[PDB]
Each structure stands twice: as C-alpha cells, then as structure tokens.
C-alpha cells in the first residue's frame, strides 16, 4: 500500500548500516526501538553483579574481565538501539568480538597452572580482533562481522563440548542449557529479520505482551544475555573443579593450621588458622580416607570417621567463639584439644 510509515523518527537521522524491524521512536521520543533498548538490562545488571562478586571472592582477573566485557557489550547495545548512529553501532558490534576473545582465552586456559600466561594464544586473539576490526571498518559489511563473531562462538562451542564429554560430565546440564537458549535466541534473531511484518502488533492489544512479545530482536537480547551469563558460569565452574582440593590436600591444611595455632603469637594468626581449619575439616569429612576406600559411605567405620569430624568441627566453632569474644589465650589453648580429638577419632583411618 501507499500510506504513512510507522517509523516516527526523532532525535537525529539514522546513520547506522542497519535498522531493526522495530518501529523507530514509536513508544517514546527519547529512544529508537524501545524494547531493543530496555531488553539489554539483563546484560548490564547481571554481569555487573558477577564482576563485583568475582572481585570480592578474589577470583582470577580473566573471570572478572569476562563479566565486565559482557557489561560493555550490554551498554553498547543499549546505546546503538537508542540512537541508531554508526558510532553507537560499533560500540555494540566490536565489543562482541573482544569479549568473545576473552571467553576463548578462559575456555582454552582452564586447565593451566595458576599464575601462568599463554602469550601464544594471547597475541593470536589480539591479532584476530585487530585484523577483524581493521577490515570491518574499511569495508563496512555487517555480515563480515556476523561471520567473524560466529566463528569464535563456534570454537567456544566445540571447546565446551570437549569438556562436558571428556573431562566434566557434571557440567552437561549447564553447558547444553547455555547452548540451547543461545540457539533459540539466534532463531528469534532470524524471525525478526525474515518475518518482517508488523501485523500482530497493528491488529490487537499493543500495550500488554500481546504486541510486545513479537519483538523478536528484544527476545534475542534476553536469550543471548542469559546464555552468555550461563557460559561465564560454566567457564568459571570448569576452573573451580580443576583447582579444587582433595582429601590429601584438606588433611594437610587442617594439620598445618593446627600447628599455626599452637605456635601463634597474635590473635590474627589464631583466628585465620581456625577459619581455614574449619573449611578443610568440612571438606575432609565428605571424603573417604584411603584405609576405607573398599567400604560403603554408610559403613560403621565411615560413620565413625564422620563422627570424629563432627566433634572436631564443633570444637573449632567453640575456639572461633572464644576468638570473636577476645579470649585469645583460651582460643589458642584449643589446639591441644583439637589434636586430641583427631588422634582419638580420625587419624586411625588416615
Ligand atoms: Ca527500526
Ligand atoms: Mg592464575
Ligand atoms: Na528506517
Ligand atoms: Na592428591
Ligand atoms: Zn541488537
């Protein structure tokens, strides 16, 4: 037909190489494509809460950068979908390549020694994103960006498939949920693109989700923001399982800290050794000592090993109580008590 377009354009002309099938400045004069802008919050707020928990918990820098990169992508999308200029378009698109390169560094370095750097992979990813950036700006074709972004997502999918198959079967539910909702999101990306018809919104009830649920590029921000959040969880869990201590480690820590308390000269050592000992005690209590590796977790010898740990833990908790009450000399005196309870109930099984 020959009628008035539904794009009620405002606040400057669209200087971007692409415009989505959401009516320009249709809800408000402030932003072009409203749901494509407000639907980016679950990619700005959740990854910002992850980056701050990751710093508080003292995690490896690369997992903090991963969460921050996803927030940078979120803000760039919110800005591209608000203005629709080329400057804010690249702030959505280019970070996607870089954040995906951070993800490939983490996924491929997950079984490496702590405090090591792979300068080979690092300069390779830096070169790939520099080459991709240079050609992307020169020849301004957005399908080149989409194929380059999509090839990093591809290697990241194969590396995550190797891990869930050969190394950590447990992460299957998370790894495949991350992938399922990302490919559902990518189906919705192609629906808003190919099925370009503002019929359902124009027909009935636009204010409730009757009209709003047919914004399939808004759904893509939800699903890919949620799928990219789940991929960082997956990545960080692969590193947590790898770096995790076993019975031999927890038995050593528990006893090292028992000697720190005995020989301690100040309140801060005593409280730290009691806290570290309590964590190692709860962890050791779950394991089966090597003398009992042939028995059931419910055997009388196993229930007794666990019983001694229960007694030991309550005692560590009593000594921590003394520490927090300022009874330093007394909390320190628990070391002899704690040695006696590992001798009487635990050490026979080790
Ligand atoms: Ca549009
Ligand atoms: Mg490290
Ligand atoms: Na337009
Ligand atoms: Na070991
Ligand atoms: Zn978008």
Image: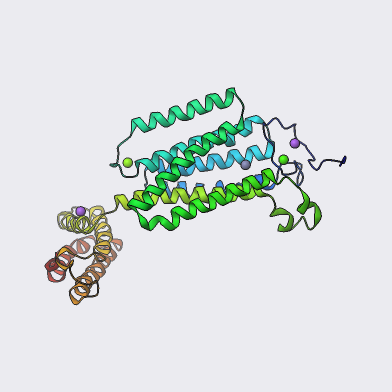
Quadrant in which residue 5 is drawn: top right
Task: Residue 283 in the image: state x and y as whole percent.
Answer: 27, 62
Task: Residue 27 in the image: state x and y as whole percent.
Answer: 76, 47
Task: Residue 274 in the image: state x and y as whole percent.
Answer: 25, 59
Q: Residue at x 55, y 33 (%)?
A: 94
Which quadrant holds the N terminus?
Answer: top right
Q: Residue at x 54, y 53 (%)?
A: 181
37 relative to 100 in the view: left or right? right
304 relative to 39 in the view: left or right? left
Task: Residue 161 in the image: state x and y as whole percent.
Answer: 41, 49
In this view, the residue in front, 29 or 151, is: 151
In this view, the residue in front, 90 or 54, is: 90
Q: Residue at x 43, y 29 (%)?
A: 126
- Examine the rendered structure and indicate whether residue 261 appears above or below residue 285: above
Q: Residue at x 31, y 50 (%)?
A: 242
304 relative to 6 in the view: left or right? left
In this view, the residue in front, 303 or 21, is: 21
Which quadrant holds the C terminus?
Answer: bottom left
Q: Quadrant of ligand 3?
A: top right
């Amino acid at each position: 037909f020959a009628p008035a377009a539904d794009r009620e354009g405002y606040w400057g002309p669209t200087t971007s190489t692409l415009d989505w099938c959401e009516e320009n400045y249709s809800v408000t004069w402030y932003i072009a494509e409203f749901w494509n802008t407000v639907s980016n919050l679950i990619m700005i707020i959740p990854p910002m809460f992850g980056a701050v928990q990751s710093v508080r918990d003292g995690l490896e820098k690369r997992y903090i950068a991963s969460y921050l990169a996803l927030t940078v992508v979120g803000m760039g999308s919110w800005c591209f979908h608000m203005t629709l200029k080329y400057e804010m378009q690249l702030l959505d698109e280019l970070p996607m390549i870089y954040s995906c390169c951070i993800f490939v560094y983490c996924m491929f370095e997950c079984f490496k020694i702590k405090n090591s750097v792979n300068y080979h992979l690092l300069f390779t990813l830096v070169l790939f994103s520099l080459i991709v950036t240079t050609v992307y700006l020169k020849v301004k074709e957005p399908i080149f960006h989409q194929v380059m972004y999509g090839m990093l997502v591809f290697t990241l999918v194969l590396r995550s498939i190797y891990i869930v198959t050969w190394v950590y079967p447990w992460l299957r539910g998370l790894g495949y949920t991350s992938l399922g909702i990302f490919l559902l999101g990518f189906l919705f990306w192609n629906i808003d693109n190919i099925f370009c018809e503002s019929l359902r919104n124009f027909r009935k009830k636009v204010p409730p989700i009757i009209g709003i649920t047919t914004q399939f590029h808004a759904w893509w921000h939800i699903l890919t923001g949620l799928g990219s959040y789940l991929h960082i969880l997956f990545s960080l869990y692969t590193r947590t399982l790898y770096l995790r201590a076993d019975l031999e480690d927890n038995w050593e820590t528990l006893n090292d800290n028992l000697k720190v308390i005995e020989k301690a000269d100040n309140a801060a050592q005593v409280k730290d050794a009691l806290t570290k000992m309590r964590a190692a005690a709860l962890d050791a209590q779950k394991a089966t000592p090597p003398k009992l590796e042939d028995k059931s977790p419910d055997s009388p010898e196993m229930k007794d090993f666990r019983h001694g740990f229960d007694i030991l833990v309550g005692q560590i908790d009593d000594a921590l109580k003394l520490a927090n009450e300022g009874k330093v000399k007394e909390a320190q005196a628990a070391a002899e008590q704690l040695k006696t309870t590992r001798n009487a109930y635990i050490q026979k099984y080790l």
